[PDB]
Image (cartoon, rainbow, N blue to C red):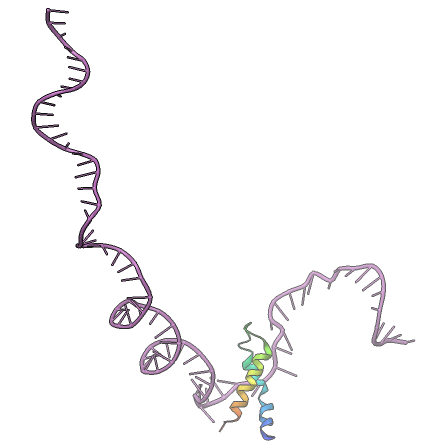
Length: 48
DNA sequence: CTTTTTTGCCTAAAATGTGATCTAGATCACATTTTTCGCATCTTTTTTATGCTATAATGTGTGCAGTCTGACGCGGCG
């Protein structure tokens, strides 16, 4: 519960970077960003 | 006196009237087979909610405004 938050805070820039490809005028910035945080945190739960 | 027109008769003849006596018709309230309908099964059949993909990738702006403006509020701004 502590240790992962480090990793989570780490790659925020990969998150936002990949997000801002499909920020064509499809939806909105931060919504893509939030769902990217989601997909991340689930990638975090599983990684080997 | 002769004609024709009429009626009545001859002479043949259809239409009228006896009602008594049946006889095939139509009624008449209530049980049975057909339509094919409606909701439950199947039962598919399609469609839909959900689930993974292990080289590697790390701070925006993003296309615009053309900036109205005069008075008054109000936070400063001294």
